[PDB]
Length: 270
Ligand SMILES: COc1cc2ncnc(Nc3cnc(OCCC4CC4)nc3)c2cc1OCC1CCNCC1
Image 1 (cartoon, rainbow, N blue to C red):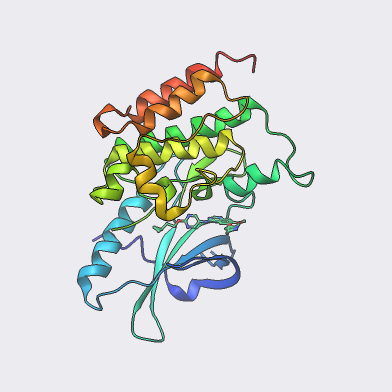
Image 2: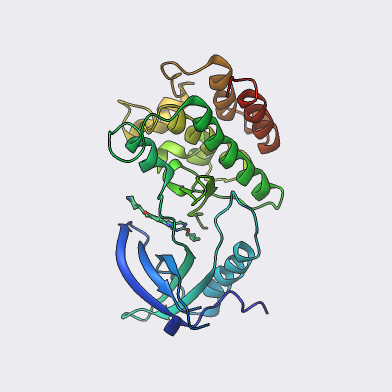
């Protein structure tokens, strides 16, 4: 067994809510860890199946993420498990607290006079370079993100982006084949990465302006894809475009994308 993943619940003090989703919530917290303390980010969830089957499979997956070590992939400190007021297991995943917050909010704030100012092209490409390196590290270990989007990418204290908030087993990030067959592969993550690239290049735009969520599958079925942004370089749009090919076998690997973006940033007068 690898029970380095389970943290004593009495070492954790829960604070103010960062956000409330359908699954769970994200909150500020303090971890005793040594007489000292540490500011952390806590993600609560609510499982099903009272028996070991569901919780052990979740624990195994938690042990996997903890044993990861890369600057562009969020580090998982541990997991506390408490039973809820209804008898349901409530796992609480503990990560380091990210003061600069998510990448999606930072991009929209770069368009406001408070906080960050205009993000130059080179800084936008570095963000993409960072996501691509973290994603490449994940696929070279056969781990599927399942929920890659700009709101799930965090800015570290040195201002390098890491991938976070992985999904387990939003329409506008889901690959065409995954909407019809519900089959999720590495190319479905490549699809989501292309959408994330478009979020960065548009500086926070919601994908497919004008198209409603319920009409997305049919829209993609007709060969429609995200339109090229204003002032977006042609070479850059062709990179994100290659992520959305109808046949997933036509999509490029994460090593090819990372190589493409790094070669483009190095071609600019940075
Ligand atoms: C200063 O604000 C944050 C700091 C964070 N510092 C670290 N982590 C975070 N979130 C996070 C959660 N869960 C996971 O992974 C779970 C993986 C497990 C397998 C399921 N990774 C990251 C933060 C979110 C923050 O703001 C949340 C936003 C603010 C903007 N309006 C919407 C809510």
